[PDB]
Image (cartoon, rainbow, N blue to C red):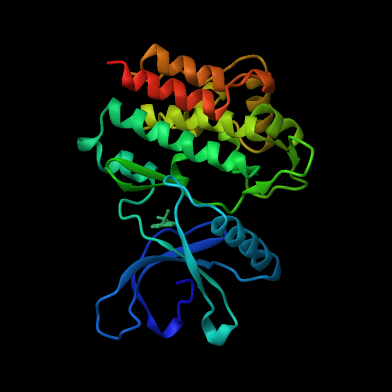
Amino acid sequence: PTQFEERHLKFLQQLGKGNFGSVEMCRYDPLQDNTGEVVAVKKLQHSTEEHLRDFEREIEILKSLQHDNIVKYKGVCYSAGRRNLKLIMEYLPYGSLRDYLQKHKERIDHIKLLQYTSQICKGMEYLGTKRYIHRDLATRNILVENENRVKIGDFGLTKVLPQDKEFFKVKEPGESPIFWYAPESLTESKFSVASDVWSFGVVLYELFTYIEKSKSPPAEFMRMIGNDKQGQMIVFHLIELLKNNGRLPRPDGCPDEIYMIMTECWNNNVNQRPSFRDLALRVDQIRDNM
Ligand SMILES: CS(=O)(=O)Nc1cccc2[nH]ncc12
């Protein structure tokens, strides 16, 4: 069922909020008896014409994906007498991977981090078979179903590659998560599978820092750059730093072999970065040995 009538969609909780849209937890109860399905409902923060068109493309992308490690599309709800649009998704109860890492450290060890790493890689391989570039791969945009399962979410920045070319030039990006971007994304606005691989390197970094106090990518890059810098000066220094092999340090407790993977993902030469298939195989081989 992809129907969802607004009058049967009942509010339970406010979840995330920020850029573009906000997400609520709702119960869908057609039989009016207080016993139905729990879902996530995504709405626009500001419903302009431009944002509506983007939201429509996000919805088409999500509907096209069926994979264990990608959040499930359930449908749309045409609310306000069908003069508004909301996206209906499955509810994953443990929130973003970023929050989960902070809140549930008691149930997380290195084996679990490698499981999550592998699952993210598998999700990304699947994206590549559709020629979708995610552009925003980060622990805040990964969702946790349970202690054994994570799913890639937020496809708001996701783009399709053209017929022939391997890069997408994003004409004029708004607010940018610059500390997850590959050098070519910073200097040329060029986004590709290879730039998602760079970002994946940074996700792997986040996992092994356990999102600890002031070890996050923005905080570490700012330390190296100089905390007194502001404005475009930050970006100028980030670029120059990255072009001459400045990199995030190995987090404390992180094996050398896992840090080597990070550093291979952070190659300035786009063609020498591993594929997501290489990474999933290598990570599952590390796990299987032991
Ligand atoms: C990341 S968040 O905290 O804003 N919430 C979600 C977004 C998208 C799908 C979701 N399913 N469940 C929660 C959730």
Q: Is residue 25 left or right of residue 67?
A: left
Q: Say left or right for 70 vs 245.
A: left
- On the image, the x and y values in percent for residue 131 come to 66, 42
Q: Is residue 275 left or right of residue 183?
A: left
On screen, 49 above or below 15?
A: below
Count of numbered circles on the image = 0
Corner quadrant of residue 78: bottom right
Which part of the image, by quadrant, shows the N terminus? bottom left
Residue with the most extreme top position: 256
Task: Tell me where residue 168 sits by quadrant.
Answer: top right
Towards the viewer: 258 or 248? 258
The structure residue drawn at horizontal position 57% and vertical position 56%, both measured from the top left corner, is: 64
Q: Position of residue 219 (x, y in %)?
A: 47, 31
Position of the C terminus, as image quadrant, is: top left
Q: Front-most of 262 and 234?
A: 262
**Residue 253 screen position, x and y as percent:** 31, 18
Displayed quadrant of residue 239: top right
The answer to whether any part of residue 263 appears in the image is yes
- Residue 62 percent location from the top left of the image: 55, 56
In this orientation, which residue lies closer to the viewer: 46 or 117? 117
Q: Residue at x 65, y 38 (%)?
A: 231
Tell me which residue sits at (27%, 42%) in the image: 147
| Picture layout, residue 95 above or below residue 112 | below
Quadrant of the rendered image holding ligand 1: bottom left
Does the rendering let one see residue 177? no
